[PDB]
Amino acid sequence: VNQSSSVEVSSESYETIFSQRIIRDLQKELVVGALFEELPMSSK
Amino acid sequence: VNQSSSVEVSSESYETIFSQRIIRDLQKELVVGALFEELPMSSK
């Protein structure tokens, strides 16, 4: 799609480097779940 | 109960692990019972 040059590439796939960094946003942190303690129940 | 599988416990009492732990709340602090001294009386 850069058609400026006479000999332009077929797709934009060939004009792009697909890095595979899997970036992520700040994701809501979690507090409520771990604060408390467990009663290892072993029965229903 | 927990009747999901062939083979089930009979009463759900054979399920629950009854505990014998007893718990009492924060329970009103008794401030004025002992603040003051005693006159050990021996008559009305």
Image (cartoon, coloured by chain):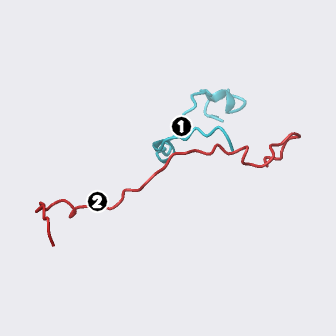
Chain colours: A cyan, B red
**Residue A30: x and y, percent?**
49, 44
Most extreme residue toward the right, as rendered?
Answer: B6
Instruction: Point out the residue furthest to the bottom here.
Output: B44
Callout 1: residue from which chain?
A: A
On the rendered structure, is B33 left or right of A43?
A: left
Residue A2 numbered mark, or none: none
Q: Is residue A33 above or below residue A15?
A: below
Picture coordinates of residue B3, whole percent (x, y): 83, 47
Q: Amino acid at mark 1?
A: Arg
Residues B20 and A12: in front is B20
Based on the displayed image, in which of its 4 quarters is residue B40 positioned?
Answer: bottom left
Q: Residue at x 46, y 51 (%)?
A: B23
Query: Which residue sits furthest front?
Result: B43
Q: Are discs 1 and 2 less than 8 Å apart at CB?
A: no
Left or right for B34, reference A6: left
Q: Residues within 10 Å of mark 2 (few under 14, many from 20)?
A: few
Q: Quadrant of the C terminus of chain A?
A: top right
- The disc labelled 2 sits on which kind of residue? Glu
Q: Nearer the viewer, mark 1 or mark 2?
A: 2
> What residue sits 15% from the left and 60% below the top?
B35
Res A6 → quadrant: top right
- How packed mark 1 is, by other alpha carbons closer than 10 Å (few <14, some 14-19, many 20 or more), is few
- Left or right relative to B24: residue A22: right
Residue named by callout 1: A24
Q: Secondary structure at mark 2?
A: loop
In the rendered view, tell whether residue A14 sits above or below residue B40.
Answer: above
**Residue B10 x/y as whole percent:** 81, 46
Calculate the distance from the C-alpha at mark 1 to the C-alpha at mark 2: 52 Å
Residue at mark 2: B29
Image quadrant for the N terminus of chain A? Answer: top right
From the viewer's side, name the closer residue of B27 and A30: B27
